[PDB]
Image: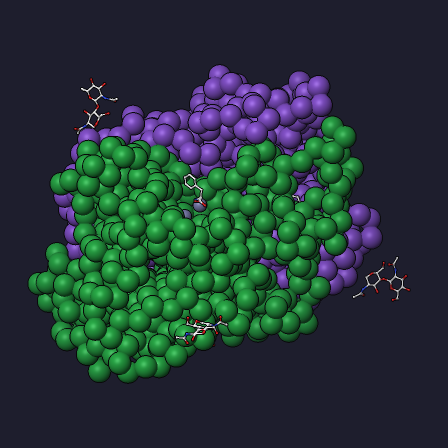
Chain colours: A purple, B green
Amino acid sequence: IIPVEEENPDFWNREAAEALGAAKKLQPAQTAAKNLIIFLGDGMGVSTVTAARILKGQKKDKLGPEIPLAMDRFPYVALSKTYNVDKHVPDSGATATAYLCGVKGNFQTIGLSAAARFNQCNTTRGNEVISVMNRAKKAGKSVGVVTTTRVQHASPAGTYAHTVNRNWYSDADVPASARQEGCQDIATQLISNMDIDVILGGGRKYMFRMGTPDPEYPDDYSQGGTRLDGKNLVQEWLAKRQGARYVWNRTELMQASLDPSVTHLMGLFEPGDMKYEIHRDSTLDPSLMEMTEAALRLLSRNPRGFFLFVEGGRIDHGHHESRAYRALTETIMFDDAIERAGQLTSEEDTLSLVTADHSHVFSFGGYPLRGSSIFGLAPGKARDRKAYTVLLYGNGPGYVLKDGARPDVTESESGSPEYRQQSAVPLDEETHAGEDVAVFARGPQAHLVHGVQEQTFIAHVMAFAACLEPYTACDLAPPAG
Amino acid sequence: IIPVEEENPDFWNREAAEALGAAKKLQPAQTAAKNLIIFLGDGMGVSTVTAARILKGQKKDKLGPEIPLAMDRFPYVALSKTYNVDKHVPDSGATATAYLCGVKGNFQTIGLSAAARFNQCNTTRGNEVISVMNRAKKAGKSVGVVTTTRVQHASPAGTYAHTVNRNWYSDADVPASARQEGCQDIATQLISNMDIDVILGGGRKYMFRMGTPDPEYPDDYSQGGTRLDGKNLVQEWLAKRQGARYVWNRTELMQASLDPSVTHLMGLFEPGDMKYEIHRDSTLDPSLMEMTEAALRLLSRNPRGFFLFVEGGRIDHGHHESRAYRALTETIMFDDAIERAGQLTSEEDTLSLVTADHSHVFSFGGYPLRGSSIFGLAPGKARDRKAYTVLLYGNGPGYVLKDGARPDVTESESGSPEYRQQSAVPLDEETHAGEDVAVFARGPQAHLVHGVQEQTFIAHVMAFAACLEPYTACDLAPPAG
Ligand SMILES: *[C@@H]1O[C@H](CO)[C@@H](O[C@@H]2O[C@H](CO)[C@@H](O)[C@H](O)[C@H]2NC(C)=O)[C@H](O)[C@H]1NC(C)=O
Ligand SMILES: *[C@@H]1O[C@H](CO)[C@@H](O[C@@H]2O[C@H](CO)[C@@H](O)[C@H](O)[C@H]2NC(C)=O)[C@H](O)[C@H]1NC(C)=O
Ligand SMILES: *[C@@H]1O[C@H](CO)[C@@H](O[C@@H]2O[C@H](CO)[C@@H](O)[C@H](O)[C@H]2NC(C)=O)[C@H](O)[C@H]1NC(C)=O
Ligand SMILES: *[C@@H]1O[C@H](CO)[C@@H](O[C@@H]2O[C@H](CO)[C@@H](O)[C@H](O)[C@H]2NC(C)=O)[C@H](O)[C@H]1NC(C)=O
Ligand SMILES: N[C@@H](Cc1ccccc1)C(=O)O
Ligand SMILES: N[C@@H](Cc1ccccc1)C(=O)O
Ligand SMILES: N[C@@H](Cc1ccccc1)C(=O)O
Ligand SMILES: N[C@@H](Cc1ccccc1)C(=O)O
Ligand SMILES: [Ca+2]
Ligand SMILES: [Ca+2]
Ligand SMILES: [Mg+2]
Ligand SMILES: [Mg+2]
Ligand SMILES: [Zn+2]
Ligand SMILES: [Zn+2]
Ligand SMILES: [Zn+2]
Ligand SMILES: [Zn+2]
């Protein structure tokens, strides 16, 4: 459909005049960032952003593409080059090293320079690269890690961990030789490497000894503790800190976040990754936005400021399943968390960056009409006389042949939360994609986020803005009130 | 392969430190743009840019992704929302209206507000929106249109034409009713709507009466004149202007561009679109870079400045064929033209924008090793036990079933200039994609290109920078020397 107001050139001329006015008003800060937030949309490439924008727009009863996401309102944009040192199409671990530690690494390692080698424990030491979050903590800031994945998953692990193998969630995953060589599982590193004030996400199971029933699924043994060393890492973490609280459900999280005596909060809401938002039990589990707010309640108390990592972690997972419905709904929730954080913080003293670790082979094509559902069929039949969807994947588990032929698809099928968009090539999991991703920035020194940059720039501009190592001689004035 | 220098964190820290230094040195101009250049990569979405960067890097014997394209060096980047008023996934005509005239339009129309309707001549009048190029000419600037497509193709036509049907190249294409209603074919509009100092690209055939042999293919009747009105539009254009020259080959173009007495130059190098660079006859046909230089030689003479449109027009065509080899080699040539223009102009007085009209359902995935060919196979077999390529398309003519199965592919096959990457859905032509495209900007007022903008912003920032209508009260100082 053609919106009538848009048929008039004045509509476009006014909008552009306003955009020019806003552009002209942008001025760089001469002051440091008190607070740092990185919002990481895992797998949230440019095609994901646009498709999510359209979906979000339509959920708000608009046509879609004209409605800004919260991230779209950020004044500064750059393109970020995501290649890992060893692979053009990266993984989450080595990209986390880039955007969290400011150094590129090798595929499937975390918090290590590219001198380290995947799954070779004996290449670890000397190659640890320290995250901006770690540097923020050393400088006296409170720090928080919030994600819809396991808190031991590759992205959040980038803020605290150093490992040659992102798969080493608990000691059960670490080969005996690596255990003897002292390569700690990620769950251990979570509680041991550094003090983290707020830890929120999934990954209960890695914290408890094998045979420990999960509190939420005591009748599903597969959800229980994984640990072989008999340690209760939650208990160990709590014992180290007065005012520390552990929560496994939403209501306790709420309670803890409002409690002045709670100085450290660990909230682990599922045994593994958290449920997709569309599957979330809102009585038991906090949304990403809620976890973000909980974190900010505690982190904001520190007069020295905070560093916060917030991950839309299952955007990535939706794309891997080639279920764009899941990828895009996760993206919207992620954008909602960005919006919520912007309400709770000031751009006068908070540098906020939104980015992705990398993209996916997700495309938005055909020639759909304005206002049509992002999950709909492209107008017109394909050359095999069957329908096709506007959303497609280059590869992944949506590839199907029924009776030797590409299956037809209906609008009813294509719109289902379980629908897998078709691909060119069958794979159990759709792949990441290697094209540049966006960086959106606002707050002190956000104007430094510009042009086309290496992904490592994300970490460096954040360290610079808050005058953290290696930029303690940042030459910035104190954060604005 | 892992480049040794990149294994050291210092490599990344130094690079980022330098990037921060460069970012900090950026300062907005207080002065106007004397010259305006828009480089339009037709179909050149973010995945195209990255894949082209890698290819270009490797052509220069580097690993690929670490080597900047000329466009990558532009300091200011924004995301541009490409939706047409009536379609989420746009065409070249209505996007041209946006980035050339600053108003969004309906799919397959050119230079018209969205009050007009595709293929309805009687909805034209009153809906004409004037291009920045036209406004530049009114302000006394010289103006140039350079493209590897027909100069009457949708993108270049955006600079001068107003039509409800981009397919109306010559009067032969215009239905009798539209001809009677005075809807001029694009070739006519090219010579009649406005004075254009330099016109370079394809589209000879639309200028000459049916039965006129093409000068380059006199023995191929299909390449001859198309016109039904008996007009020689080249002769008409020449007759209107003293110092006007028409050329149909490279050597005459060279000659004309160096000739002080040549004030107007029309160079039409093929009957229709120009050959892909990989097929170009370098004795008969100028590359895009050469056409760009020729144009700049003439345009730069005017003390009031110039507006120049330069299009990498067949990037788009390569993707439609699902021949990434063609899309990417066109992209490199386009980037070479950008580089060449930057050598011949000063960013002190020239605002240059590089953008795309829209993207394609082109993806770069699998998990290829650093330094591997962009046209190679993804490591590892697909679920059907056959190989697949790192480059894929969501849809398009690369979809194949041999003996009811997806064909296997070899590196030799996949690397061929004729190879069509596989897709999920067979279509005669692969489709455009609707995700945001990049805008790169440098020169006076380039800092205004930021954040996420409507595609119309491109036209408006250019008009603003050169103090053209509607921004004659730009309040900028005269262009810097
Ligand atoms: C990391 O450990 C591996 C042990 O697997 C070492 O690899 C061995 O190196 C020796 C000498 O080069 C070879 O003869 C063995 O065959 C290798 N073992 C295996 C099973 O791969 C490697 O040297 C160690 N790296 C470091 C940095 O100490
Ligand atoms: C959220 O977690 C809290 C803390 O574990 C749960 O509270 C416990 O619930 C059991 C069963 O009702 C009681 O016997 C304990 O006394 C409670 N402990 C505390 C500290 O209150 C609470 O039930 C959980 N919420 C849900 C919906 O399961
Ligand atoms: C453009 O021309 C078309 C002629 O095709 C006009 O459409 C006609 O309008 C009348 C009255 O609405 C209908 O009864 C006819 O059936 C239409 N003709 C056809 C064949 O479509 C249209 O009105 C014109 N638009 C403008 C702006 O004048
Ligand atoms: C490029 O175009 C020029 C101009 O049309 C061609 O020059 C003509 O060539 C014919 C055949 O040799 C001569 O008889 C004419 O005298 C030439 N005209 C002029 C004005 O020089 C030239 O041949 C073309 N180049 C190529 C390679 O075809
Ligand atoms: N990122 C995906 C799968 C993956 C495999 C290999 C490398 C990178 C990613 C996941 O963990 O859900
Ligand atoms: N923003 C959250 C607040 C919250 C914080 C902590 C736990 C739960 C909820 C909400 O909408 O509910
Ligand atoms: N842009 C393509 C095909 C196309 C068809 C319909 C709409 C837009 C584009 C071309 O002209 O080569
Ligand atoms: N840059 C062009 C110069 C040129 C201008 C005009 C015509 C032909 C060539 C070249 O490399 O040849
Ligand atoms: Ca739960
Ligand atoms: Ca030729
Ligand atoms: Mg992640
Ligand atoms: Mg074009
Ligand atoms: Zn990821
Ligand atoms: Zn992933
Ligand atoms: Zn196009
Ligand atoms: Zn096209």
Query: Which residue occupies the foreground of this view, B177 or B229?
Result: B229
Residue A111 location in percent, x, y?
60, 58
Residue B357 location in percent, x, y?
38, 50
* Left or right for A89, reference B143: right
Q: Residue furthest left?
A: B473
* Left or right for B367, reference A20: right
Q: Residue at x 55, y 66 (%)?
A: B281
Q: Is residue A277 visible?
A: no
Q: Quadrant of the N terminus of chain B?
A: bottom right
Query: Which residue occupies the foreground of this view, A427 or A114?
Result: A427
Q: Quadrant of the C terminus of chain B?
A: bottom left
* Left or right for B91, reference B7: left
Q: Is residue A120 visible?
A: yes
Q: Residue at x 53, y 56 (%)?
A: B219
Quadrant hosting residue A56? top left
Quarter of the render that holds ligand 1: bottom right
Query: Which residue occupies the foreground of this view, A314 or B210?
Result: B210
Q: How many marks?
A: 0
Query: Which residue occupies the foreground of this view, A291 or B100?
Result: B100
Residue A226 location in percent, x, y?
71, 35
Residue B209 location in percent, x, y?
35, 51
Height in image: A281 above or below B178?
Answer: above
Quadrant hosting residue B31? bottom left
Q: Residue at x 10, y 63 (%)?
A: B472
Q: Residue at x 34, y 48 (%)?
A: B227
Height in image: B5 above or below B177?
Answer: below
* Left or right for A29, reference B387: left
